[PDB]
Length: 192
Image 1: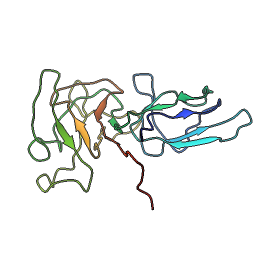
Image 2 (image 1 turned 60 degrees about the horizontal axis):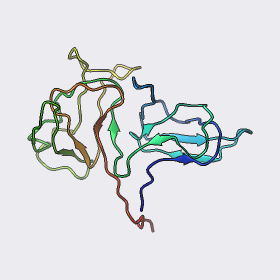
Image 3 (image 1 turned 90 degrees about the vertical axis):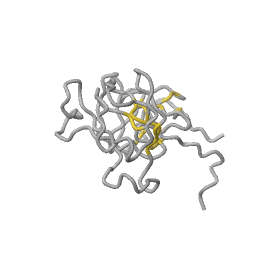
C-alpha cells in the first residue's frame, strides 16, 4: 500500500518536539519550520516510547506537552502530498517563480489556479539558471511579508514534484499551502 497517511501514536502520553523552532500559525495550529520535526511520545514515567520525523510541511495536529490519546493523528500529510506550507498570510509575487523561465503558464480563473510544477535541485532545466525557484511572500499592503521572529522575508523555495496553482495575485491565510510534494513510494523496495 505504502501510504503512511498519519502517525497514530500508539499509546497515551505527552508530545515533546525536540530540535525544532516552529511557530503557531493563524489557524491555531503549528507550522512546520524545518526538517527536524522530532515527534517524541512519552509515558507517565517520562519515557520516550515513540520517536518520529514528520515531513517538513506535514500539517501538525496538536502542540506540545498535551497528553495525546493513543492511535491519534499527531500530524497530517496526504499519501502523495509532502507539501511546503506557508506560515503567515501572504501574496504570490512572481520573483524567481517567473513564468516562462521556470514553468509553463496555464492560467486559470479568478481563484487563480494552474497546472504549473516546481521541482527540486537536480530536476531543473537550463532556462531559469538565475532563477532559484521560489515564492516571494508579501502581505496585503505589498511589502515582503515576514515570518514572525526575524527580519528575513518569508521565502519558501518549494521543493520537488510540488504542483502550484495559486497564480499572481492571491492572498491566503496562515496555514495554507504554497505547493504540494507527492510521495508515492508504493512497494517500499529501495534500500540495500
